[PDB]
Image 1 (cartoon, rainbow, N blue to C red):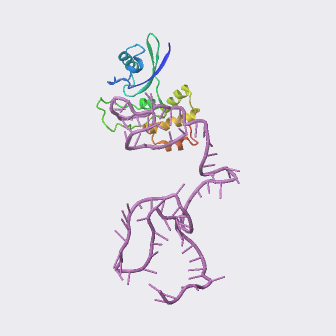
Image 2 (cartoon, rainbow, N blue to C red):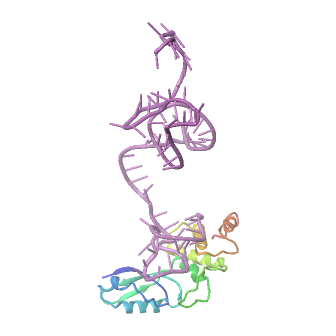
Length: 153
RNA sequence: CGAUGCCGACGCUCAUCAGACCCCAGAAAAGGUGUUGGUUGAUAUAGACAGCAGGAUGGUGGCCAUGGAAGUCGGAAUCC
């Protein structure tokens, strides 16, 4: 029996207080083993929370990582990760490559719930300032850059 | 209690605590869709104000965060 469930995991870091026993417990498979398998299957994220889908059968489950738009933005932003102490004001400072935004727009077009590419670049660059970074200037600069100088295929 | 017993003029006020003339014998801040005026800004045939009903969604379960907070506890943010 196919059962699709959503789990917002903390990434490669193993969380102490889990939220796996009420959802997976009555199905049968061990939630500690589920958390260990998700922490092994993430691997390269190591910092962020990802809404991973799990397709559970009668025998065992399968893990499918679904990256969000903000998840891809903070994945593209490469900072050194810190410890469990988590020092305050860890808000992101840097510069996002525009080709990375093009790649995220192509992946969101492959997921295919949007307008065509001109809309996807605008909405992902609008989520970029909600993440809190800028491509050599903020969103009103890229609004001016979109006018008569677009780079849409 | 002498004198409006003016064919007086115009408005305001209803008080289930009305009000009625310097000192002086009583009243405040805060309120009222009670009613009478004034100041300013709106929208209305590109169809307003009430009135009876339908949607109120995607990027996203946004990033710091907390045992947990997925728009509906805080603070930065607050765009397509």
